[PDB]
Image 1 (cartoon, helix red, strand yellow):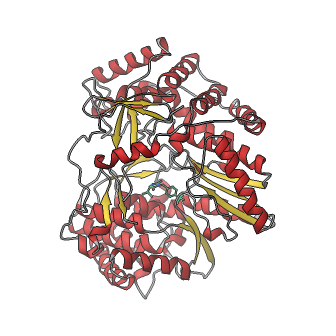
Image 2 (tube, protein in one colour):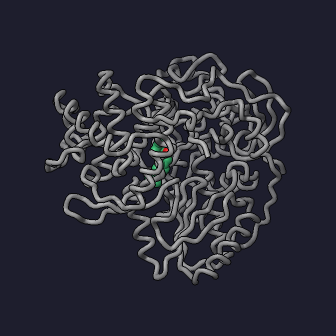
Image 3 (cartoon, rainbow, N blue to C red):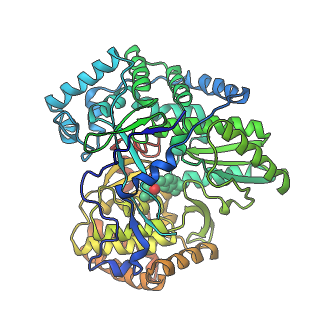
Length: 557
Ligand SMILES: CC(C)[C@@H]1NC(=O)N(Cc2ccc(C(C)(C)C)cc2)C1=O
């Protein structure tokens, strides 16, 4: 029962890979300690292969089956629709990997007869054949980090034609089923502000709250055939068209359960018997499986009044405390149960008694004050990785602008406001690129966003208090200040001076640009303005946002 079998053929790149931080005239204004920042490349793929290759053993008890029967009962209330070829095509990212069958993501989106005819052939093949493993491409991801160096993460994905077919069969399923099954526990239904609220209310709802996060070591490689067949049985509980039931069974047997691994050169790298990281069902399957194993492990450990919060493999549990020594014992029994279920830990879970000290989705709750002096809870994170990626993006154009996604997701934070907003608005001003739409990622999905719409977006997601937060906690301020020293990022006093300039420059341009100046940089002036709601913010269609997670799902809006 190995997660993977290998042939020895290397995981190869598509193009030239850069590992060292590229430097330009703008680099030193953001970060001075260049040797701290690196990108992962296919060079390190071999080390990741060793890490993800292990034997999985599963022992399934009555808690597991009891939780599963309940999840199936809730899933049986879902009615999912089959997406048309047109709907599935328009959800394809413009720069999605081209098919091996002579058409690309632009041909898909434009409904070109060659692309549509190939789509109808893969579809016909899925209905007629439920046995033949579907070929996948294994590629090393190029991701930027700060040191103290990780090996490249791997992406496993099927051909463009299959990805469009996954959309037709399962887009409605993966978008509606997890919230029905898990209710408030499904993390991807919340905006960052709704998440902070969910976490604070849950913590408050316990008499003696105890919280922990559970890190499953290499979650995708811990996922067994059983887990993948169990996810399918959950999907089949829905009220589906018979053609969809057929495509779901077929995609499960032929792709989701496993298949051969092919490099960018066309060589067989080996075989996968675990979760594929680049399929439509990666996020949904991981969230359902993580929730099933943890809900069963909560019952095994006899955890009192457990509230879970699940986003793929990211798991947070808020429960009733039985005192520090019993809680430590409860977590050992929880870990033992998770291990038996084939979800062993990376770092052992640690009980926490301060909500602010709990990290989930690489984030923690923190407190600041709005203009009226009210204590406002918001979500933040260690800024090291957002800052290292901002440094890379300062010198290289990338298919996914992390800085824009970070400004959207972490708009009320000290570091996103003072550094990210200031730095990138300065760059866009100098290049006259404020109106240029940039692609970013929100819950794994791709969005093309105009930076000029940032104030309207921030207002709708976080409220006007995002533009007015002050009096950040000493814990938060010190983490940011330490991070800046570590990376050689100028101190925050430099950023406030620079932001006054970025603000004056945005105001000068008038219109949408002045709106960015007025709202985004109101913190930088001593004589603050009274910020009122933006009329355009109500006109924004923010549906599709915070409904589901689509990490590795090839989704564009
Ligand atoms: C921020 C951006 C670079 C990118 N987009 C996204 O949804 N995540 C994952 C993510 C980010 C924030 C959250 C919170 C906890 C703030 C809702 C959850 C998941 C990313 O890392």
